[PDB]
Each structure stands twice: as C-alpha cells, then as structure tokens.
Length: 66
Length: 66
Image 1 (cartoon, helix red, strand yellow):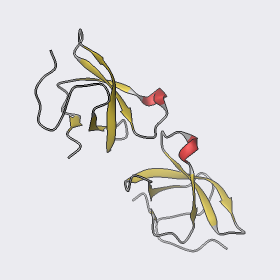
Image 2 (tube, rainbow over the protein chains, first blue to last red):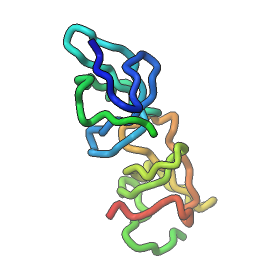
Image 3 (cartoon, rainbow over the protein chains, first blue to last red):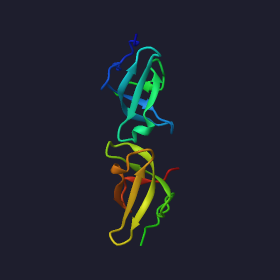
Image 4 (cartoon, chains in turn purple, cyan):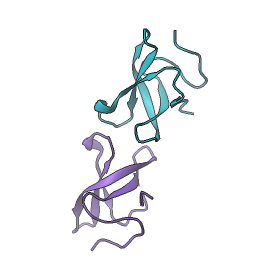
C-alpha cells in the first residue's frame, strides 16, 4: 500500500519533485505505479522519457512540489 | 562578435547554466552559434531537443556553470 507522506499523492498524474541523476531537485509527475515492489515511475518535466525512473515510494529523493 | 563574460565560453560544446521555461537554473551546453543575430543554441542536459532554445549571448538567463 502507498505510504501517507505530506504534500505528495501517490497517484498517476500527481505532481511532485524528485532528485535527478545530476543531483538536481526538478519538477516531476507519476506516470505509473508498481504496487507489488512499492515503486513509482517518475517523469522529469520536459525530459527524454529515456530518463524516466522508478523510485521506491518511500524514497527521500522524492519531495512535495510545494 | 561573442561577448567576454566570466565563467562562460561562447563555443559549441561549452558548458554553462541557463534558466529554463519553468524558471529553473539547469546545466546546459552550446549546440550552435548564430554570429549574425548574436544568439546561442542552448541544450538543457537530458531534455527533449524539442525544448533546445536560442538565447541572445548577452542574456542574463545564462550564467557560468561554476
């Protein structure tokens, strides 16, 4: 089950911020949810979908967009 | 002629930071130079080249990467 974290909604189309591979906090959204392994597919706004990434929904590298 | 600005080299393949369409300072590079209109083609690292942009080489929306 997705965890209850402030400012974040674990839903496809939900907006948040994630820390990218270049160690930059950038605006992102949830493209898909893997309820079995507890992961969220993250898409960094205006990036090649080649760099979309799966983050454990408990990752501290995810934060509210506000 | 390109201007002389600290930390920035007006050369194809040169690295810097530019302020993107989402008002975020993000690492970028010079893909091309237009010496007639005094513009630089900017590519934001890991983005769709659809969002590469021409910036006047005097733009304050360009800054050194350091």
